[PDB]
Image: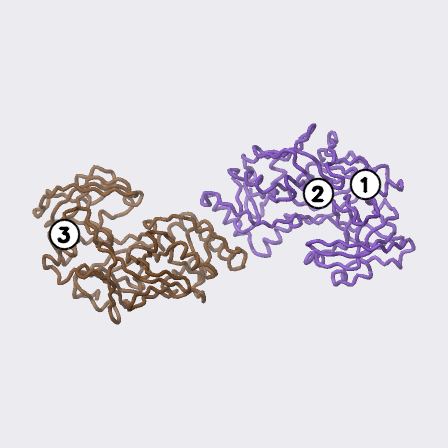
Chain colours: A purple, B brown
Amino acid sequence: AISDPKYSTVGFNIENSYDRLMKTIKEHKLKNYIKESVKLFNKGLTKKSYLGSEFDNVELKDLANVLSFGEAKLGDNGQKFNFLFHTASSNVWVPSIKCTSESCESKNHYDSSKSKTYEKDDTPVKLTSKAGTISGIFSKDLVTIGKLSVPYKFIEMTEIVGFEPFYSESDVDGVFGLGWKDLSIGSIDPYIVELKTQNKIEQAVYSIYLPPENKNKGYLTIGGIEERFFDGPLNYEKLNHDLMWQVDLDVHFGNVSSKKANVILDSATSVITVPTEFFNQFVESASVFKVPFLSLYVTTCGNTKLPTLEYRSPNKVYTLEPKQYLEPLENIFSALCMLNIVPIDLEKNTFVLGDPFMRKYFTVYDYDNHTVGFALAKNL
Amino acid sequence: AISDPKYSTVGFNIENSYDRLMKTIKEHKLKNYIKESVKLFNKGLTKKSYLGSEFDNVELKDLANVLSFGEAKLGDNGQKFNFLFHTASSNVWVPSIKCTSESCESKNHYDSSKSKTYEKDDTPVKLTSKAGTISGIFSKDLVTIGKLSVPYKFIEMTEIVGFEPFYSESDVDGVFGLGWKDLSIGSIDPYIVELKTQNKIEQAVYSIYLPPENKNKGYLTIGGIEERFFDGPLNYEKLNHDLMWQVDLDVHFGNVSSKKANVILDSATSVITVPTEFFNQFVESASVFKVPFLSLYVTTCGNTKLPTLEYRSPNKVYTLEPKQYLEPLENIFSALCMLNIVPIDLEKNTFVLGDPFMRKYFTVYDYDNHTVGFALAKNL
């Protein structure tokens, strides 16, 4: 599995929601506030129960974990970079030595002149979004993830505006795409597909293994199914979108349910997400406490009312028990836990399976067949 | 004034809102919750500012202090009772020895057979209200408040239902009326008026002096103006109701105002009251913090934004400064204070002047002329 695997595996690090929350709690000295508020809840003195969930952040990007690793290299001189994984993009992105922005100054840069394997492309490319704007150009070189290498067309970034204060504060240089969506109109296959095209791997598939007992770690395996990660069979579901790791499922949280939901698999999302209305029904008379002024839902670890979460397909149900969707806060209050489930309205009837789901289910992402696979993860 | 006065004066004790709040805080162990919530407010982390004032108690009786004293006697044998003062009732009420209720069992009773001065009346009488029901009968005997005595028709109570858990928990036996409203249709003058009728006093007037530095004490003076309680002139306002200590005034709290308000003088009310809408405008951007889940508005003692409260008549303005409407909570948090101002909707455009007002203004209640008088209280 992780000691001498069959297919190429790389470890990656995760900054998670627990970590960010603890930072915020130390920063603002919030521990006693939280403790004293919970005590109030337990005495029956918060009432009848009010709705202070809005706190419309809302942003899916407020919920993103940073999945990063530093073992990928560009060119025959193996120029080193720290990359975060993005499950929706199919491009690789790095700062250019020619980057004029202040953001790029402390970052590792790609310098096409130092690599004998560089081939010029120069096709200009630009992302503009609410969070920020990146412009650069395509360049071709060797992209190596340890054991695997292929000549590949990535985006060399010449100007980066926004993505602050995160980008400057992070050690991350660029983004490595494990998705389907190419910014070009030149039909640049994902890195994983190109490996198969060039016969570097048997199949255009990868898996994510998130170990149950290390929430700062995950493992990416490329080019085959490493069976030592999981118990029992792999079940497969068909993608319901040509360019997203998204499937059709009926969602039931106890008596609260939604049929024909769109359910996106995104291991970089820090939590399970549900629509807001759906969430409200869920937490109502479930004895969960919203801490005033914080985006934080808490309850006792042994809460006997919390149901199993069910994601139903025509031939398999995936489930999460309370112990997989609660996070212990023992360092704040004995037997206190938080909900790793957040209300957020996306596309209608759209749900996200983030880190909590993948701590239970080993997941497989199959470009060749347009499927995702699920199996019970082993505890390694 | 209080050492050998000119007119008959009696001291009375007050259980106030501060005392009840501190009891509640000890009971439910709330000090640290309050402290930690305030700290949150001061860090700028409660936002933008939400409305959790409802908390529609609302009840004017949730705000009543208990003004009590134990020096009044009935009959020639001087049967002892503990009475609370009620500023709207004109009757005296005591438990009968014939009271069948469980409420009456621990109380002092009137026993008409033990008094040589009793004269039978037996006219039945009954109060029914939301808080409870009292039925009894009129009886006539000597009613003595120390220096003053007069044969007087009071209500002997034979059945008391409700008024719990207060009545059983209190040492109070009955109610002594300092108001205008008689339950009979036999035109029973208030005790104070009857004293004048029988030439026990010069005039049917009384005053309330509430000493600025003892919030558990007040003094009632009957039959004249004791000038050693106050500085400067007495100003008089005409009652705008035949049977209430109520006047016409324009109310301004900073830029928030209301013209031709009905303003009731009731020293037994624990706070200043204003309409809810009026209050909301007042506290908005005034840097006052509503503590979640408690009926409690707090702010720093030196708050430089808090305005003077103004109650305007055609020839006088009565005012309260922040220091007269804030109550220090130094035992919870250094330099923290609470607002002694509560939102409550009564009769439209009706306001109440309770204890905070009377800690600044010595007040006079004049049955002969249908006026109330106000002067600056001395600090004795």
Q: Give the SS element for disc 2.
A: loop
Q: Quadrant of the N terminus of chain B?
A: bottom left
Q: Residue extending furthest left?
A: B116
Chain bearing mark 1: A
- The CA distance from mark 3 to mark 2 is 84 Å
Q: Amino acid at mark 3?
A: Val
Q: Tell me where residue A157 sits by quadrant.
A: bottom right
**Which residue is pictured at 14% across the width and 52% down the height?**
B143
- The CA distance from mark 3 to mark 1 is 99 Å
Instruction: Respond whether the residues carrying marks 1 and 2 are from the same subunit.
Output: yes
- Residue B244 lies, in percent from the top left, at 24, 55
Q: Quadrant of the C terminus of chain B?
A: bottom left
Q: Which of A12/A157 is in front?
A: A157
Q: Amino acid at mark 2?
A: Ser
- The CA distance from mark 1 to mark 2 is 16 Å
Q: Amino acid at mark 1?
A: Ile
Q: Which of marks 2 and 1 precedes in the sequence?
A: 1
State the mark number for residue A222: 1
- Residue B5 lies, in percent from the top left, at 18, 65
Q: Which of A168/B179 is in front?
A: B179
- Residue A72 visible to an observer of this rendering: yes
Q: Which residue is tagged 2?
A: A267
- Residue B105 visible to an observer of this rendering: no
Instruction: Respond whether the residues carrying marks 3 and 2 are from the same subunit.
Output: no
Q: Tell me where residue A120 sits by quadrant.
A: bottom right
Q: Residue extending furthest front?
A: B260
Q: Which residue is tagged 3?
A: B143
**Which residue is pictured at 59% across the width and 55% down the height?**
A26
Instruction: Decide: few, some or many residues near mark 2? Use Cα within 10 Å; few <14, some 14-19, many ≥20.
Output: many
Q: Which of B195/A106 is in front?
A: B195
Establish if B282 lies above or below B174.
Answer: below
A274 to the left or right of A233: left
